[PDB]
Image 1: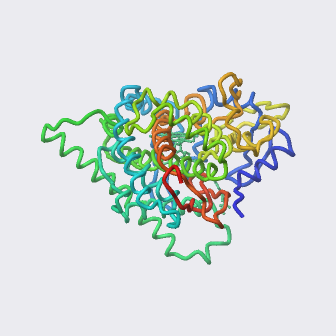
Image 2: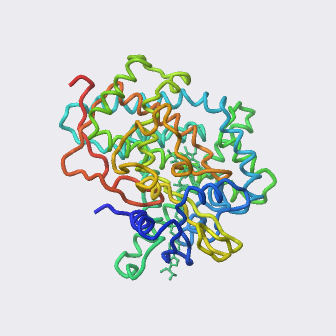
Image 3: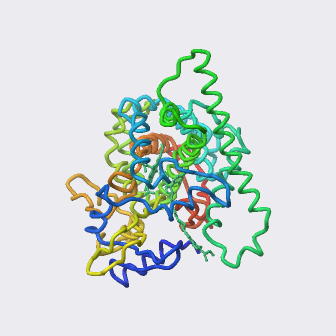
Length: 436
Ligand SMILES: CC[C@@H]([C@H](C)O)n1ncn(-c2ccc(N3CCN(c4ccc(OC[C@@H]5CO[C@@](Cn6cncn6)(c6ccc(F)cc6F)C5)cc4)CC3)cc2)c1=O
Ligand code: HEM
């Protein structure tokens, strides 16, 4: 069964009102599920991330993973310094110029799949979408080619896989430390060091090029380095390398996987997606930036996919002074937990919440008001939002143009939780070419 901790929180939120104490963490924390509260705490620089919660990202099993990178830096000043600089890499011109990378990798994904489109060969969409998102990220952020889509870098994607399973366990055990052997523990440490070392090398390869007076176009890497000029160590730079290395591919992959998974049982939705893709791009191969804006219906489908299946389920702020929240006195020094997964599944905020219905986001439908935030909100919202929404439309658009998917019998629709929420089963499918 693929219930996650988020599902328990949901149960408790429906039953116990909009402020609920939990005791699964470092502390009595409080899960906060009223829209007004979401607005209050997220939409204000006055509230900041809980350093105690994000320590699980800082280091893992004694090994430095995300450090004080852009996600896990809780101190506002130190965080604003990083964010000002790194923001330059996500300008509109910065993103428009990634379209070629997004197209190249999307195209390459589809060809690999058309090569397997006999209707018998089982293919892990979760693996495939992961390879694609990784190849996009490496090229787009770091100027490097991983070619996982071409069977390359098996150790790299092994290190990522273990690091992530490692995060799952780093939360837990829990009496389960006698059974789950030292093998897993040191493999995770190995993996985490593998990742930092890839960072060291790609920082090297980059510095080498600049030293030969070579011309390097402005980059996420360019901006992470610049955020680090003056530092005694490269250690704050590696934090940011690893953060972007994982954040910039894993959750885009989960989102793609959930979308393909859910679409496999929504034939009407699929037909309408096909109809839209036919009129916007036809059978043309490259999608321009202007084309993405016109995939209106595809936007709604993805928004709806993020409402039921948000990979990044929420966030935590620290409540420093005792405050009254929805009629409940909550003491100072208390961690607040926000969940877009929880709120998206409450019939209080969404009629018939288990029905996948993209019309909820149709033009003219009032936007959800603090009941939906798959990219978080306020100052600590996702820097990579537009980047993600772009690449995901590029991939999904191409799949829809050329392929049809059928989920392999015995594949489940349920969730697991690693660093993020993702499908429990890979998304094993057989494929045919569109029109069969
Ligand atoms: C027995 C022991 C016992 C005692 C000792 O008795 N004990 N005592 C205390 N606890 C304890 C304490 C704490 C927990 N927590 C449970 C989980 N928590 C947690 C924190 C942060 C989270 O952030 C999620 C990231 C955010 O962003 C993403 C997504 N994303 C955005 N853009 C792109 N990707 C992201 C970022 C960067 C990347 F690089 C990749 C990513 F995907 C995902 C999520 C969860 C904290 C630990 C549990 C138990 C015990 O168990
Ligand atoms: C569809 C996939 C994506 C979703 C659902 C997602 C969602 C989120 C959310 C919920 C936050 C977490 C904030 C918190 O812990 O409170 C966030 C932050 C962040 N994400 Fe994304 N994201 C995705 C893709 C991107 C990609 C492509 C990148 C990089 C290119 C990335 C970069 C980051 C970083 C650096 C932050 C921290 C920003 C800051 O605190 O200033 N994400 N993401």
